[PDB]
Structure formats: C-alpha cells, structure tokens
Amino acid sequence: DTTPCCAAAIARPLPRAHIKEYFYTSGKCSNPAVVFVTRKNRQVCANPEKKWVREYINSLEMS
Amino acid sequence: DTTPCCAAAIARPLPRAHIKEYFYTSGKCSNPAVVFVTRKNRQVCANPEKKWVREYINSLEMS
Image (cartoon, rainbow over all chains, first blue to last red; front, side, top):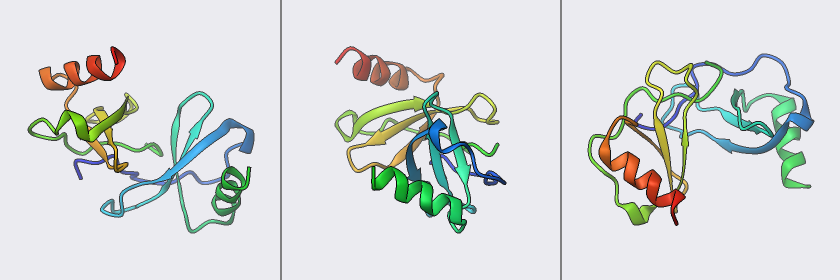
C-alpha cells in the first residue's frame, strides 16, 4: 500500500475507442480494480466484476 | 478519484536494475507520487520530491 490503489470504480462504461491498454491493480488494495489507460494516458479505475469491463478486456486481448 | 492513487511512498530507494518504466499519478491524489514499474510489473509509489527518484527518472529518460 506503497502501490497505486482505486478508492472507487467508474459507474458506467467509458467509450471503448478512448481506451488503449489495461492492467489490474495490486490485490493488496481494498477495492482492487481494473485500470483502463486512455489514448490520452488517463488511468481510470473500473469494477472488474462488471460485464462491460470483461468484454473491453476481451477486446484489447483479442485485437 | 476513480483513478489509481498512492496512500504513501517507498522510504528508501529500490534497486535501479529492478525498474523498467515510470509514470506520475494523477495530481487529483492526496499524495500524488511517481510510480516505478519493475521488470516483474510491480507498481511502486515513490516520493517525487526525493533525490533518488529524480536521478532514476533522469536515468530512464537519458537511456
């Protein structure tokens, strides 16, 4: 917890074409999240347990 | 604060050869930090105002 962590997680989907990369936060966070990195390099915390996250991820991985 | 943030920041220097990338957290954090990404993809929060951070960074940028 000398590692970057997500207090909360984006309500609704961000636009799929704003998004270029993802990673998962440490599991040592209290809300471990997925993080989306936008073409503009904003890092956005998302709720991994949510359908739009899991098809965005599937989308970035089956490019 | 739907963006990944650093509660605290690594006391002492990490080994320079463990470190492959860096970025700065959002300025919207309460402790906005530098984050070091290790060859093993651990993200480590560091205090930007600290001499070892600023020559690690200079090191990754003058490669």
